[PDB]
Amino acid sequence: LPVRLCKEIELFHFDIGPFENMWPGIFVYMVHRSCGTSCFELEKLCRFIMSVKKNYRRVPYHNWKHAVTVAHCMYAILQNNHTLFTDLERKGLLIACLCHDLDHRGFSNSYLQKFDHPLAALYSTSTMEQHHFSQTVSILQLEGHNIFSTLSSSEYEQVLEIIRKAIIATDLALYFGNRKQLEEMYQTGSLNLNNQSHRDRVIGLMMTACDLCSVTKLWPVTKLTANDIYAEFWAEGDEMKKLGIQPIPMMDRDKKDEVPQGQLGFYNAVAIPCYTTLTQILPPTEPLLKACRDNLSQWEKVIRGEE
Ligand SMILES: CCCNc1nc(C2CC2)nc(Cl)c1C
Ligand SMILES: [Mg+2]
Ligand SMILES: [Zn+2]
């Protein structure tokens, strides 16, 4: 990792994209700058990182690159909101982010529930999210992978609960209600970060903010990531067609023209409210909202023909 990266990595808009070979090392650095060099035993941490990477499939979007990008956004939020979180939450959230899409197979919760896949019989709601957490626990259970071994049985349970709620929160179906609740608590002046239920909701919104952070990068980066997002959705659509089912337009590769309009709908219904609410609760996260608005403007320009 070069000396030029050390200061860039602190910024919310930082793109890990051009530094693939350095991704494991970038994650270690973020952990060290967040909870110290003695936060985890370096040998166990590397073993855990490398096993997490191998357990992310070669799919167009929910892959290793997405995991590190999400972890980096969490790091930027934590760095700009220091004193707010405990050592356990700092540790827990960075791990949750790296593991939030573990073993994703390129299929949505919609597909798995519609085609009655065994994962949907096991987990009726937040299907893949319940699987991602189960995979995180399995990796921790492996020999020489328990990074939380030094913690007491009480601290271990706490951090696994932090991780569990954080991973489940990445289910976008749960985001709508979470954000409406947080906006209510904030507007009425009842929001209290000392209150555990309020704290869990804030962490949940932080998770959504990180998960969707490709919409907060510089326009060239945001656009290339959207291409990977649609390549994965189109592959699911192709599978649906083979099963005699017409996919939704977003998952249909023959309905490409609808993408800029779909992005506009996504930013207005999901991304803008997410970062607007996050900015209200955590004022230093304002650059994420500003970057999201800039990308919304770029999508409007694509629709108007100025692509
Ligand atoms: C499963 C990925 C969830 N994330 C996103 N989903 C969409 C859908 C196409 C409208 N757009 C964006 Cl930009 C993101 C980040
Ligand atoms: Mg996910
Ligand atoms: Zn994700």
Image (cartoon, grey):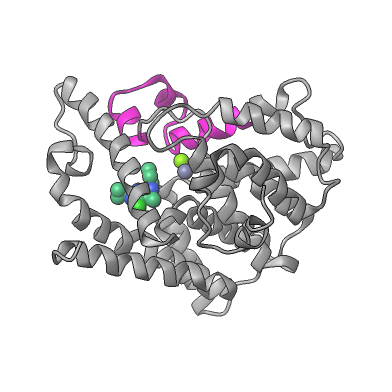
> Looking at this view, is 121 or 50 the one in front?
50
**With respect to residue 7, does 185 lie above or below?**
below
The structure residue drawn at horizontal position 47% and vertical position 26%, both measured from the top left corner, is 57
Count of numbered labels shown in the rendering: 0
User: Where in the figure is residue 193, as x and y percent of width and height?
Assistant: 67, 67
User: Where in the figure is residue 149, as x and y percent of width and height?
Assistant: 83, 33
> Looking at this view, is 180 or 22 the one in front?
22
Residue 218 picture quarter? bottom left
Which residues are drawn in magenta?
Answer: 108-137
> Looking at this view, is 294 or 132 the one in front?
294
Check if residue 68 falls in the magenta segment: no
**With respect to residue 28, does 140 lie above or below?**
above
**With respect to residue 62, does 212 lie above or below?**
below
User: Where in the figure is residue 172, as x and y percent of width and height?
Assistant: 41, 49
| Residue 162 shown left or right of residue 236 in the figure | right
> Looking at this view, is 282 or 261 the one in front?
261
| Residue 42 shown left or right of residue 107 in the figure | right
Residue 303 picture quarter? bottom left
Check if residue 127 falls in the magenta segment: yes
| Residue 257 shown left or right of residue 187 in the figure | left
Our reading of the magenta stretch's main secondary structure is helix
The structure residue drawn at horizontal position 37% and vertical position 47%, both measured from the top left corner, is 225
Query: Where is the C terminus found, in terms of image quarters?
Result: bottom left
Using the rendered image of the protein, determine whether residue 78 is visible from the camera's viewpoint.
yes
Residue 111 picture quarter? top left
Using the rendered image of the protein, determine whether residue 194 is visible from the camera's viewpoint.
no
User: Where in the figure is residue 43, as x and y percent of width and height?
Assistant: 80, 31
